[PDB]
Length: 50
Length: 50
Image 1 (cartoon, chains in turn green, cyan):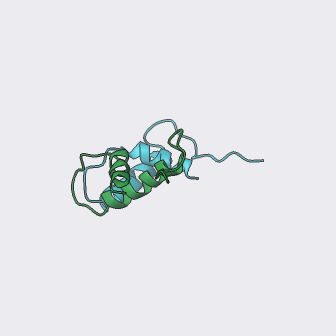
Image 2: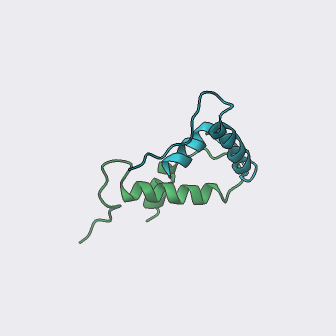
Image 3: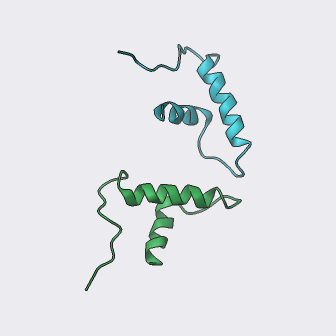
């Protein structure tokens, strides 16, 4: 019986936040336009999808 | 035992600021969208990466 986790996180130097930065600059630099969401909104969406 | 430096800088006519202008108009004119950072933010990022 398990709980899905993003890993431990205490600050922006966490691997989930560095991954949020990496995936947000991948997605934002592939989509023409001004986004309305930040990197943390995209990673929280990406965990809710999990 | 050395200290890495951007060169001497007293105003915007400095070579680090002219280089900031040059690299910022290279990066901004290759990326579709409205940036949120200025030229000085990009050059300070580019020195922190060094």
